[PDB]
Image (cartoon, rainbow, N blue to C red):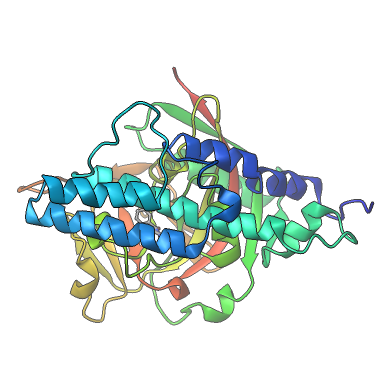
Length: 353
Ligand SMILES: O=C(c1cc(Cc2n[nH]c(=O)c3ccccc23)ccc1F)N1CCn2nc(C(F)(F)F)nc2C1
């Protein structure tokens, strides 16, 4: 009956992130089974078991047990987390990247279970359904105007920090929302210095969970080696580096990027990955993974109290002698109270070919 009371741009955002059918299609692309394991009846416990099975696998990988041991651990994961490979013979997880794949799958399942719950919630017919979904986020989203000063600056942040080795696409900013998640400013470590406005990209299936529950710490059951710098919340200062984690396609060229205030405090700087980076803090507040190019310094503005690392980017003269060197920086915090969500960008990806 009742007409939406939401701004239209917010109505389109809600419609886009609460699209269960699109999640269904995103999981199907990660080789998952949407009917045998219907997202409508996902539970935390199915996902917890998921993590547990990935831990057994990590154990085999750490022991070099790539025979029967690993074969059975992978089958238990594929049983608790139903996959649909049709005729293909379900493959072994042995590499870090294969492992990382599964973790990203469980994170999306977790955020999809949050989303499903919310969209099925009550169904009070006093308010438009968009309106209900938006209240249930407990997260304010305010459409800023194309002319607005904020749009100007974030546009420049997005374009100015597009990395040159991500030449497979450009990005156009369609819309910009101010985010105010209930409780985040109250929780936030305003005491800590070195507060930066940084990027976070995720699959389109995770935004309801991200906006409703915040960026979360990975559960204890998950394998530590899933995480290059441990179980924390990961941000970049380069737009495209985050944007790659949106997993946008030529057919699905619309994604979302997040800007958050991040209370870095004192960074523990690392050159190479280390899943156990969190124990190496010793009083420091964050991990910084160090890359070859990063925004300058001289272009850094500020915005409601956070330093926006605008570009152009520049060589940092960083290089790792004995192993891999990250192309771009990477920042990890190990507590949600070091994150305050600020903006949500609606972004068109324009793929070269
Ligand atoms: O931030 C992360 C996280 C993200 C990535 C990939 C990634 N993505 N995007 C970016 O821009 C980005 C920028 C730099 C580096 C990497 C990234 C790799 C590991 C991570 F730990 N997490 C917090 C949210 N979260 N929630 C859960 C759960 F499962 F509990 F629900 N697990 C997590 C994990």
